[PDB]
Image (tube, rainbow over all chains, first blue to last red; front, side, top):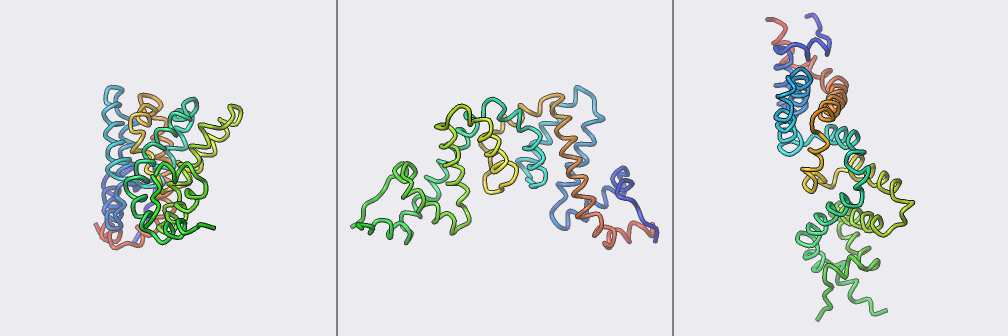
Length: 123
Length: 122
């Protein structure tokens, strides 16, 4: 047996496809998938960009969600996201979390022991 | 039998809101209340404090924390940051981070995998 460097595996579609199937076993194919899609992107034509960027957002931030990927995204676009409109962005998220708290948790809280104990505080 | 608080009264009251917080902590969800409090703090703070508090909240709830699917709220605004050139710069930087995760955490186990031995005798 002779041993392949990480770089040679990734820059070779044969080996890279195989590494893909290993990651599929641990339900992680999306990491390789993201890597391939990002490589495809920096050597595509200008015309192809909006579509491939859209396809990648769909595939890797709504249809799948690896945390390492989300971490990097949010780090790099912070200034774009909240440089100015910090208040308006947080306000929009707050409205959505408000609705989840109200519809999904508040009702069960009301029948919780913790809520009954709060109510028999007449001291 | 029992006095029933509206959702609104719970959130606008530190006593009731603390209690609702502990109920959520039980089911490992206290970050939803925590996020609500931090956002309320923000829109009623002093103007000088804002950039720093926005920064600290972004760090706590986008970068470091897991329990809020932030992206549900903001699909358009995130994609607006990915248009044209910014898109390439950002995905390239994400790819570099993923490159390092692949290299450090998975490649080594791949190398000792059955999949790798089968690849070699060809």
